[PDB]
Amino acid sequence: GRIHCRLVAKKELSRDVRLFRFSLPSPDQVLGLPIGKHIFVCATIEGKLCMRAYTPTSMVDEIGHFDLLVKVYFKNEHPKFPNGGLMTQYLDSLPVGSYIDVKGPLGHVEYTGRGSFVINGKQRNARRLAMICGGSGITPMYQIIQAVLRDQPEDHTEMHLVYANRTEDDILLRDELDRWAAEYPDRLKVWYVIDQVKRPEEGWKYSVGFVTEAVLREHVPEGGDDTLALACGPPPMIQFAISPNLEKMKYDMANSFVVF
Ligand SMILES: Cc1cc2nc3c(=O)[nH]c(=O)nc-3n(C[C@H](O)[C@H](O)[C@H](O)COP(=O)(O)OP(=O)(O)OC[C@H]3O[C@@H](n4cnc5c(N)ncnc54)[C@H](O)[C@@H]3O)c2cc1C
Ligand SMILES: Nc1ncnc2c1ncn2[C@@H]1O[C@H](COP(=O)(O)OP(=O)(O)O)[C@@H](O)[C@H]1O
């Protein structure tokens, strides 16, 4: 089922990331999206109506609006993908006032409370949570990462994050993560891995490069019992950069591996 939203405001955080501020058909409500799930921002472009999943980054109780952190895929920017992304340039193309119409809640992972998951049906639980995402696949994580902190401190779920990118200025939710990182070290381990390093004149200490066994070993809870791994990054990243290694750390690669 649909809901009629309206881009009430928008912000250009940088040369290609925008913070879109939508408003709900009714001021007295919240998006009410269940932690672990997502919403589809529908639109008909060219002739085809195309669904795209997006996980808002607003505090689950914001009344009257929801924010979307979007990284715009421009055409004339990449050799392999010369024509940009389909739903992003259309969104960067909407003037504040336009209506959009979402439809949730989709997905299959839901953080039902404390360690207690339910994947593809099965209720579950875990204390050590392994998180791995790159670029935009962090929002699916952030919602969770934000939910445990808001359950402080009876939610003892230990979360271990590895957040991949291409450059330092491309680390998305960073101030927020480096803020929490300090507040709740007893439960959130943050580690940045980056492809390049714009200016080391400054001094980048985190890893440089791709995500790999060493990185995983020295950063992600030993694949044991009551230890679940969640991941959200480009297909390749998962395929051969995250999938095999988590086996190499003895995780039950069959029921402990969920992917948004
Ligand atoms: C759970 C979940 C949460 C998500 N949340 C967010 C979110 O909060 N914010 C957000 O910004 N995204 C999020 N996404 C991403 C979303 O599904 C999209 O595929 C993406 O936003 C935009 O793709 P597009 O629609 O613009 O079109 P498409 O062009 O279909 O984009 C996908 C393909 O084209 C490539 N591509 C095209 N142009 C480029 C380019 N210039 N540079 C690099 N690659 C390019 C993509 O990398 C990939 O191969 C989420 C996805 C999931 C599943
Ligand atoms: N072959 C791969 N192996 C390992 N990780 C990958 C691979 N391909 C992409 N990734 C990682 O995930 C990130 C890509 O995120 P994505 O959503 O494509 O947008 P962008 O390409 O702008 O970063 C890269 O920074 C890279 O670290």
Image (cartoon, rainbow, N blue to C red):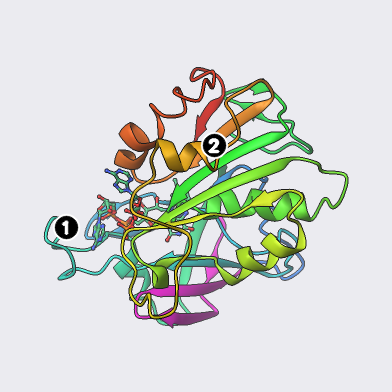
16 drawn magenta: yes
Residue 45 percent across, percent down from the top left: 28, 60
Q: Residue at (67%, 60%) from the top-left corner?
A: 181
Q: In this orientation, does residue 188 appear?
A: yes
In this image, 251 relative to 59: left or right? left
Q: Nearer the viewer, residue 84 or 44?
A: 84
Q: Is residue 26 above or below residue 163?
A: below
Give the SS element for disc 2.
strand
Q: Looking at the image, which residue sits at the far right?
A: 154
Q: Residue at (29%, 65%) from the top-left corner?
A: 73
Q: Is residue 130 above or below residue 228?
A: below
The residue under label 1 is: 81
Tell me which segment is drawn in magenta. Answer: 1-23
Q: Is mark 1 within 8 Å of ligand 1?
A: yes
70 drawn magenta: no
Q: Which quadrant contains ligand 1?
A: bottom left
Q: Is mark 2 within 8 Å of ligand 1?
A: no
The residue under label 2 is: 230
In this image, 203 relative to 89: left or right? right
Prevailing secondary structure class for the magenta stretch in the rendered image: strand
> Which amino acid type corresponds to the residue marked 2 in the rendered image?
Leu
